[PDB]
RNA sequence: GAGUACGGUAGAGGGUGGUGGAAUUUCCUGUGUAGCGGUGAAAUGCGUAGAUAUAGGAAGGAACACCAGUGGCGAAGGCGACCACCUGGACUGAUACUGACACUGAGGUGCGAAAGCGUGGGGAGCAAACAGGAUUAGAUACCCUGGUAGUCCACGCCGUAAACGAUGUCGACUAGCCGUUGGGAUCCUUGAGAUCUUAGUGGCGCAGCUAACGCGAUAAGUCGACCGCCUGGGGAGUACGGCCGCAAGGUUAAAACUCAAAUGAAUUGACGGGGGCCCGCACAAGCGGUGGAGCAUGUGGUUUAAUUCGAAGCAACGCGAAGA
């Protein structure tokens, strides 16, 4: 058991778009602390999104994450000597973070040339709601709505 | 164990009155006690502890 | 066919393992019935209040084809779903005239089985 | 002291017959359609020949929900639906009567839970045995599905229980406090409480006792009458004989041998698939890994002439060695 309040880390806004929402997306796509390398990916990705349709690469990011962020999720829970996967709502602080999770993870496993156009490829592919990250969202939503029997916390 | 729904009230408060009638009659406790057969030694031992706690 | 019955009676045979909802007339002639085990809930999910309301809601819409709008609720037996099945009857079109517990109470009659030594 | 006569009170005290309600099961009929039942989950099982559910009817057996209460009655074992009949005791008030007629009690005799046994009935539920399904390495079990004796009744037998308050019966005395049952007396005649007293039934508690735990007017305190019983543990409440029993068995009841302890209470610690509270990358959420591949190192094993010696779970294995 713990008594700690953990820690409240703050993220500074991105320098090219003035949106802290991209800052945690940058914070998510990180590998080995290479800040400069990864930010070259998103801006190149956002240029690809902007160059292919749309009007602003920042607003389709907003459109992308809601289609990825689930509204409910189960967790392993033991009450009566057995595991009951009680579906629980996802808090606003976690839904966007896990939205940033599933965009990079499934785009990393795509077959496109480089991540620069691979996260970009998923960005519009997820904004319209027909991508694998969108697919992963609904099966989690499929995991719930079937275990609805267990609703005690 | 029997309630009548009146005019112009929500059915929700009709439910809450219903179980309030149920625990007043204590039907759930009665069926729980008759689920299995409690031997006279176990029944008298339970009632002796009930008297001790009451005092 | 359509019996065209306006007044009915709903019976919920809630048990510790299953909940059987049966809609009947004032003379005890059944029209529709559904069970928690018949609604895709098997095992640990059959004994859950959510499975009870699914059974009640499934039999609820099957009972409107007779043109039933009034019914009395006769819940019987203990278990998770004695009330959750009744709340399902409110979601679909119905008004409940009365709710009654008809759980049988022996007056110290037949000997029950022995304690389970689990 | 013990007892009798009278009025009254409470009671699951006992026996003999009726009667009632709830519920279970079985059967008949109507509606109605894919499950019911069960479990941790399943399966055996029941069900399309129509189950479960629901409604109406019928049969049968057993126990009497609520009242219900360290409440009541009984020598104890025990006794819970209602009513009628037969019947024992206790408590209570005064007066009247006998006048020690009392207590205990080896033998003896009577009653004595449940199981069990015999003859005859009865059989709804439950359920030894038995059968099947699970679980398990196995499971002659726990769990599930069925299910026979039995449980019920009458008449006999048995005669044993942790038959316990693990405390024989009877009588007297010894601070109090708080409940409760059946009475009685006085203030309250109160409408409605209070104070004494008695027979029970409980909880604390002075003294006293106790190895301690605890008992403490319902004594395990202070005494008195009588009775039963004990003399280390195992062997053994066994063998043998006697008595009893239809039997199962009961009762009375040893020795050889063997051990130096068995035992009671309480304390500290430790432990618990006991409980309560709290913490730690212990768990949860994630970041990246090992285990798959090639190379470096150490260890075990093997081999050698030696493969020098030590380190061996966490807390040894890139350790002594910060460098054959």
Image: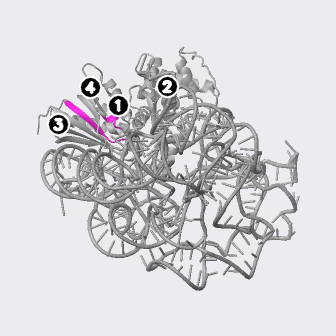
CA gap between label 1 and label 3 equals 24 Å
Q: CA distance from mark 2 to mark 3?
A: 50 Å
Identify the magenta region: C70-85
Q: Residue A91 shows which numbered tag?
A: 2
Q: Quadrant of the C terminus of chain B?
A: top right
Q: Which residue is mark 4?
A: B5
Quadrant location of the N terminus of chain B?
top left
Q: Nearer the viewer, residue C76 or A73?
A: C76
Residue B21 - label = 1
C-alpha span from label 4 to label 1? 13 Å
Q: Which residue is mark 3?
A: C26
Q: Do the dots labelled 4 and 3 sit on one chain?
A: no
Q: Please name whichever residue, D174 or C68, is drawn nearer the observer in this view of the structure.
A: D174
Is residue A132 placed above or below B33 in the rendered structure? above
Asked if both marks, 4 and 1, belong to the same chain, the answer given is yes
Locate residue A18, reporting x and y percent. 54, 14
Q: Nearer the viewer, residue C32 or D88?
A: D88
């Amino acid at each position: 058991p713990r008594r700690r309040v953990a820690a409240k880390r703050e993220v500074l806004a991105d320098p090219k778009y003035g949106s802290q929402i991209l800052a945690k997306f940058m914070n998510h796509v990180m590998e080995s602390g290479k800040k400069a390398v990864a930010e070259r990916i998103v801006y190149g990705a956002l240029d690809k999104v902007k160059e292919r349709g749309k009007a602003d690469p920042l607003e389709t990011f907003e459109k992308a994450l809601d289609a990825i962020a689930p509204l409910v999720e189960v967790k392993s829970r033991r009450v009566g000597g057995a595991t009951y996967q009680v579906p629980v709502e996802v808090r606003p602080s976690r839904r966007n973070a896990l939205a940033m999770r599933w965009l990079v993870d499934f785009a990393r496993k795509r077959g496109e040339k480089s991540m620069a156009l691979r996260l970009a490829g998923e960005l519009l592919d997820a904004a319209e709601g027909k991508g694998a990250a969108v697919k992963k969202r609904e099966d989690v939503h499929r995991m719930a709505e079937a275990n609805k029997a267990f609703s005690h916390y | 164990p029997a309630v009548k729904v009146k005019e112009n009230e929500p059915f929700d408060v009709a439910l809450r009155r219903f179980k309030r009638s149920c625990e007043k009659a204590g039907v759930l406790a009665e069926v729980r006690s008759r689920e299995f057969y409690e031997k006279p030694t176990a029944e008298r031992k339970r009632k002796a502890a009930a008297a001790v706690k009451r005092h | 066919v359509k019996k065209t019955v306006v007044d009915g009676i709903a019976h919920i045979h809630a048990s510790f393992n299953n909940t059987i909802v049966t809609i009947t007339d004032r003379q005890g002639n059944a029209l529709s019935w559904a069970t928690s085990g018949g609604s895709g809930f098997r095992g640990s999910r059959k004994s859950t209040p959510f499975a009870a309301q699914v059974a009640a809601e499934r039999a609820g819409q099957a009972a409107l084809e007779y043109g039933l709008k009034n019914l009395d609720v006769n819940v019987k037996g203990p278990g998770p779903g004695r009330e959750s099945a009744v709340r399902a009857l409110n979601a679909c079109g119905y008004k409940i005239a009365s709710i009654t517990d008809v759980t049988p109470i022996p007056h110290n009659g037949c000997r029950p089985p022995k304690k389970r030594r689990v």
